[PDB]
Image (tube, coloured by chain):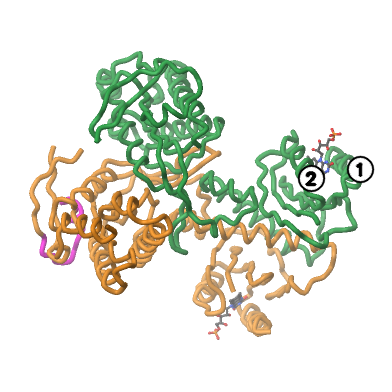
Chain colours: A orange, B green
């Protein structure tokens, strides 16, 4: 019982790789091809499922290539695609045969475009593709999730005073910090909504959601004093709202336009809790449901009941206390660029 | 000096070899050369020649019956040498080539291509437009542009998600997105993203009339949809409210290397979303700002809804958007239906 997987990755040393591959693939009864064109890697692997997943696990951690996307996984294949090739390496760059020049140039234009599109896809969708699962045909399921929401404090004022490029530098720097921190703790960013970041966590990731929130506030606090006063990054603040509940996670839309979205009351609650941090001396606020997903011991602070558009309990942690004032900031932002 | 463009498309031998006959004859009288390759129901074509000769030719290929979902991937300008000087139009049937050496390239081309096709469906319409124009969307700078922000969402959606089984909520939301995306695109709008049950789109400042007709068409097609199905279908309960605004917004792609997204930043984006919720409290399913009103040339029968705290802004609508129903009785009827 064998399987076949195909992946692309971003890059004489290659000849050393192919010879080591022929050595190990024979020993592991693995067949397949490695093709490379214009600094790109294309490899097809096939063999028994145990020995293949053992091999692919090594190649994912290889130094020489990165941006490794597994496009297709075949299970229970009937016949080997290349039964005689332990690991045939094909340098498409050196191939000057004029009957393959179109297909070779088409394999580049489509692959270059395919990587550009990958950077816009939702994180969950890319995960589904790496697992050999067709994202269009995955039944949306009801799952218990922690909803994350973070946006820039007083962003309306910042668009008024700053020129366009400084606003874009700022918004990009904010998204970059959020995504890297969220992804590092295991959270899945769903989409950017204006200046708002939306992510989710599994119900066992209550501590990671709180720690992600604290780490984002920390990385922004460092950035503000790490740069000069004229740098617009000196004005970057955030508030974060978390919520727990059941949501429908899946792919909605038409064949024309499709997206990955979460449907549920908790989505709006986390968004409304986030906007509440403008009126609290805490850059973080979450429901009691998030509080009950946390195994670790936090010094939880009760902020009372608040009416969210009946009133729910709102909490925070002692680490997330603001040293500044929300009004002091909107003034010091307006007056800095005044 | 010539231009060269590449595109993929989807199929709708003797019927196809005929395309080679007609095209070879014209490509020489047009001083055009290129290759046409097809594999597992997909079309690939490269072209080159004087710009005027290619622009007029690609316009004919764009409206051809025998293929659909055409996407131009690459476009190079100011080239010296033709990549294929010998062939006015050489067809290649990769489904009928099995030289051993070509098998890896062939299997890789269909896989990468299918995957590419899937990714397009998730791409924002604006990113696809930049790809069609041959412009790398990753290197484009965001700019301040004047837009009409479109906002619409499903009425009483919190009630439906509670009463309906999960698989039935999906059908309703898919159908709603399907109707909105179809109408918004047909009027020259760009769906920018779905936000839960919410649809956000944008129209240029010359499309004020297209923005209103888009909103009335969506209300019309849902009203038609409601009485087209049975009363036990979830679609019998699908209503909508729409809000529009006009203002300067920063349109452009943003994000890190990990995640990129095309988004709109501006005061008007929030102003539009507040109007879509204001329709709950109005006898009209549509509500737009006075800025949208000045983008319309058609003699609309505008209705003034006064100023509204959001400092206050003027709210307008058209008589065609009048709700033939009470909004509050609808939220009651939806509950007492699935109850
Ligand atoms: C593009 C690429 C293709 C590779 N192909 C193979 C392969 O076909 N077979 C294989 O065993 N390893 C392959 N590798 C990875 C190396 O085998 C692996 O990183 C290393 O040789 C581990 O060897 P070791 O067992 O001595 O520790 C590939 C790596 C890259 C970057
Ligand atoms: C996939 C495809 C590729 C085509 N490529 C060319 C082409 O390269 N040159 C050309 O003259 N016609 C090409 N055609 C034909 C045009 O679609 C058009 O129908 C044809 O030029 C009709 O010629 P007419 O203007 O005399 O009616 C192509 C058609 C298809 C379906």
Q: Is mark 2 within 8 Å of ligand 2?
A: no
Mark number, residue B25: 1
Characterize the local packing of mark 1: few (<14), some (14-19) or many (20 or more) Cα atoms within 10 angstroms.
Answer: few
Instruction: Give the chain of mark 2.
Output: B
The residue nearer to you, when weighing A40 against A333, is A333
Q: Is mark 1 within 8 Å of ligand 2?
A: yes
Q: Nearer the viewer, mark 2 or mark 1?
A: 2
Q: Which residues are magenta?
A: A286-300
Q: Residue furthest top?
A: B324
Indicate which quadrant contains ligand 2.
top right
Instruction: Quote the CA–CA distance across marks 2 and 1.
Output: 18 Å
Residue A299 versus residue B279 in the image, above or below: below
Q: Secondary structure at mark 1?
A: helix
Residue A258 versus residue B315 in the image, above or below: below
Tell me if B189 is positioned left or right of B227 in this view. Answer: right
Tell me if B224 is positioned left or right of B269 in this view. Answer: right
Tell me if A244 is positioned left or right of A142 in this view. Answer: left
The residue nearer to you, when weighing B193 against A263, is B193
Residue that numbered label 2 is attached to: B52
């Amino acid at each position: 019982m064998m399987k076949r997987l195909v992946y692309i990755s971003k890059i004489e040393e290659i000849q050393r790789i192919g010879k080591v591959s022929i050595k190990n693939n024979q020993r592991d009864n693995i067949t397949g091809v490695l093709l490379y064109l214009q600094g790109l890697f294309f490899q097809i692997l096939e063999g028994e499922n145990e020995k293949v997943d053992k091999l692919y696990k090594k190649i994912l951690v290889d130094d020489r290539h990165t941006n490794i996307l597994c496009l297709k996984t075949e299970y229970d294949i009937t016949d080997r695609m290349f039964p005689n090739w332990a690991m045939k390496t094909i340098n498409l760059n050196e191939n000057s045969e004029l009957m393959i020049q179109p297909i070779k140039s088409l394999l580049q234009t489509i692959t270059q475009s395919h990587r550009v599109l990958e950077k816009y896809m939702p994180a969950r969708v890319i995960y589904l593709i790496n697992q050999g699962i067709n994202p269009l045909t995955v039944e949306p399921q009801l799952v218990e999730k922690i909803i994350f929401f973070s946006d820039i404090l007083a962003f309306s004022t910042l668009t008024e005073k700053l020129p366009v490029n400084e606003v874009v530098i700022l918004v990009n720097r904010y998204f970059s910090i959020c995504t890297r921190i969220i992804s590092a703790y295991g959270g899945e960013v769903t989409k950017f909504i204006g200046d708002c970041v939306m992510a989710s966590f599994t119900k066992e990731q209550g501590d990671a959601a709180i720690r992600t929130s604290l780490d984002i506030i920390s990385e922004l606090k460092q950035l503000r004093h790490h740069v000069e006063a004229t740098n617009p990054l000196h004005l970057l603040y955030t508030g974060i709202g978390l919520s727990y509940g059941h949501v429908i996670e899946g792919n909605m839309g038409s064949s024309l336009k499709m997206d990955h979205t979460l449907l549920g009351d908790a989505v709006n609650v986390a968004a409304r809790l986030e906007a509440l941090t403008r009126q609290l001396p805490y850059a973080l606020a979450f429901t009691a449901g998030v509080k009950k997903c946390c195994q670790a011991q936090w010094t939880f602070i009760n902020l009372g009941a608040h009416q969210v558009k009946e009133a729910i309990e709102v909490y925070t942690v002692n680490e997330a206390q603001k040293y500044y004032d929300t009004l002091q900031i909107t003034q010091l932002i307006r007056q800095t660029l005044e």
